[PDB]
Image 1: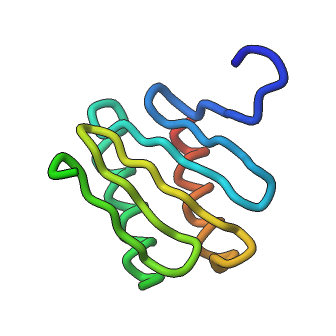
Image 2: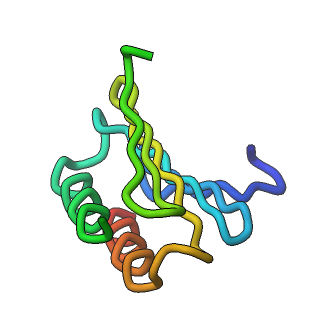
Length: 48
Length: 47
């Protein structure tokens, strides 16, 4: 929310909720540049 | 459940896709630092 929030918005449709060590990234493919989504999916693929 | 996908890249790195939304769960105590840093770099350039 607006007060005491662990959620940060980098851009519309791109937010991160911090939960200590764990974090949740919400990415809206209708709003976040496709290039950004692909770069992130590429990084995740490498982890595999 | 036919309206989404769930995938695990490594322990502590899983994603849920539903509609236009991509929800990535990252456990930084289990996912390599390099990986987390490259993702953060991408988000910041977006800012």
